[PDB]
Amino acid sequence: PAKAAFDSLQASATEYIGYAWAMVVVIVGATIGIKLFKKFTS
Amino acid sequence: PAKAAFDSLQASATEYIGYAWAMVVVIVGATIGIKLFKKFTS
Amino acid sequence: PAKAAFDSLQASATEYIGYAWAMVVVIVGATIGIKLFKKFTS
Amino acid sequence: PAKAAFDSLQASATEYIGYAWAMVVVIVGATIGIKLFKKFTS
Amino acid sequence: PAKAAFDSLQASATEYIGYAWAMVVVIVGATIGIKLFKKFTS
Amino acid sequence: PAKAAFDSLQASATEYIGYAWAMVVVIVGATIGIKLFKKFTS
Amino acid sequence: PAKAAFDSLQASATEYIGYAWAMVVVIVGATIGIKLFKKFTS
Amino acid sequence: PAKAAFDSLQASATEYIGYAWAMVVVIVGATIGIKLFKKFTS
Amino acid sequence: PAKAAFDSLQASATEYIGYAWAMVVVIVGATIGIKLFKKFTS
Amino acid sequence: PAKAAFDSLQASATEYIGYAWAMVVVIVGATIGIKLFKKFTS
Amino acid sequence: PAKAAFDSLQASATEYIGYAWAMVVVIVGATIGIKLFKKFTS
């Protein structure tokens, strides 16, 4: 029953992974733009 | 009879092992993509 | 709860990133103008 | 007669032992491949 | 006559003991190899 | 506290940048006038 | 301390620049008068 | 030391310039007189 | 060495200039006398 | 070589000039005599 | 070639000049005789 549960979840792992991606999109965005401002200044 | 049963199953072990592999495909997928998003951000 | 918290923050990362950008606007400004004065002199 | 019977069997022990080996080949296979999938994911 | 007979046999005990050893070589072989297959799998 | 400190300073960067500009005004002045004397001579 | 030192010097740059000008007055003088002699001749 | 050396020379430039003038006096003389002879002839 | 050479020559320019003058004496002579013959005729 | 050539010619200019003079003797002759005939008539 | 041509002509000028003279002989004749008639009358 546990193996089957893990199968259903796997897929679940894919859901989490989809979310990953967005949060890191914001973090990577940060920083790229603002460091670019710093680039201009230098 | 038990030894023979184990022979039939072995093969059974191979079936389980085939399944292994997919579930871990999802888990390894997770995480690789989303951590890549984080990489971009950094 | 922590994953959700990180979602709320992401967005938070975007806030920080917006700020980045201005501070580096000042630093990049500095220096561009004054180095231009030096350019004239040379 | 029993000692002689055991001699004939010994050899018999070798037959069993040959079989051992295959069943455990499947079990060890299982698991190595699928755990490798998990490795990729991580 | 019985004591002397036992002397002749002793030696006889040594003959049996030589045989022991081989039969148990097969049994110990069995099992070591096949359990090693299982080790790989795990 | 450090981010806020940097905000206050930015502005600070602007102060430095204002100063830049004058020092380089003198250096660029130098040289333009005197090289002009040399121009006359040639 | 170095920025302040440069401020004091700037002004220093202005001193050098004042001198420029005279040396080049002599060089430009040279040559203008004597080339004028050559002009007469031609 | 080089700037000072150039100051001493400037003046040096003035010496050269004084000489200029004489050599070109001869060249300009040449030619003015003799071309005048040609003028008479024409 | 070249400046000095030019000094020696200047003087050289004066030599050439002395010669100028004679050649043009002949050319100016020509022509003045013969055009005078033409004057008589007219 | 050209200056020397011109020297040799100058003299050459004198030759031409000698010729000038005769041709214009004829032209000036013309005209003086015949205009005198006209004078008589008037 | 033109100078030589002019030499040949000069002489040519002398030819014209010879003719001058006759035409003006007629004109000067005119007038002297007839004005003499007028003289008688007065």
Image (tube, coloured by chain):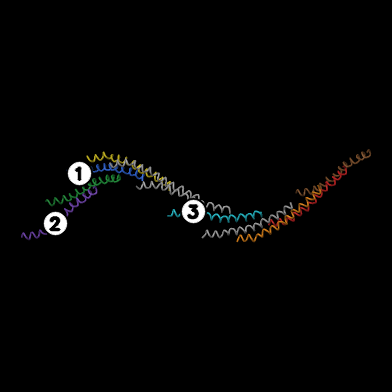
Chain colours: A yellow, B blue, D green, E purple, G cyan, I orange, J red, K brown
- Residue closest to the eye, B15 or B32: B32
> x%, y% of residue G6?
46, 54
Query: Residue placed farthest to the left in the image?
Result: E1
Give amino acid for label 1.
Phe
Q: Measured from the top left, where is residue B13 in percent x and y?
A: 23, 43
Question: E13 or J39: nearer the eye?
Answer: J39
Q: Rate crowding at label 2 as few (under 14), some (14 to 19) or many (20 or more) other CA atoms within 10 Å.
A: few
Answer whether residue J23 is visible to the viewer in this image.
Answer: no
Chain under callout 2: E
Q: Nearer the viewer, mark 2 or mark 1?
A: 1
Q: Position of residue D39 (x, y in %)?
A: 29, 46
Query: Disc 3 designates what residue?
Result: G11
Label 3 sits on what residue type?
A: Ala
Marks 2 and 3 close (CB-CB < 8 Å)? no
Q: Dot 2 corresponds to which residue?
A: E17
Are discs 2 and 3 both within one chain?
no
C-alpha distance separating marks 2 and 1 = 36 Å
State which mark lies toward you, 2 or 3.
3
Task: State whether discs 1 and 3 lie on one chain.
Answer: no
Q: Quadrant of residue A9?
A: top left
What residue does disc 1 label?
B6
How many labels sit on residues?
Answer: 3
Q: Nearer the viewer, residue D31 or A23?
A: A23
